[PDB]
Length: 33
Length: 50
Ligand SMILES: *[C@@H]1O[C@H](CO)[C@@H](O)[C@H](O)[C@H]1NC(C)=O
Ligand SMILES: *[C@@H]1O[C@H](CO)[C@@H](O)[C@H](O)[C@H]1NC(C)=O
Ligand SMILES: *[C@@H]1O[C@H](CO)[C@@H](O)[C@H](O)[C@H]1NC(C)=O
Image (spheres, rainbow over the protein chains, first blue to last red):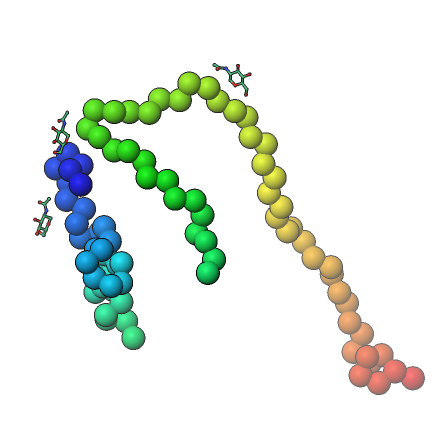
């Protein structure tokens, strides 16, 4: 995941969590209900 | 469960690039509605004719 220096960790999906969603998607889904 | 298409893992490295060597002309079709059937309704003959 070395794309020259850009860190896409906040937009790439996280395989550790059971729901494969980005860290931003978690906040987007945990605030709209 | 419906499939979301094929699964292709493109190789990404800092030194490799993919350059196309040939091409193709694709003639696709796209349909778009423009107008509809203009309808004129008679009030009296529809509500109570004769
Ligand atoms: C990407 O950003 C996160 C949050 O700042 C950080 O924890 C992580 O170490 C960064 N990763 C890289 C490749 O620097
Ligand atoms: C490409 O990135 C990888 C991961 O940082 C690194 O190990 C490798 O040496 C890099 N190659 C070049 C050509 O910089
Ligand atoms: C390019 O593709 C066509 C078929 O679409 C083929 O006839 C032609 O030989 C190819 N040319 C090259 C540059 O390989």
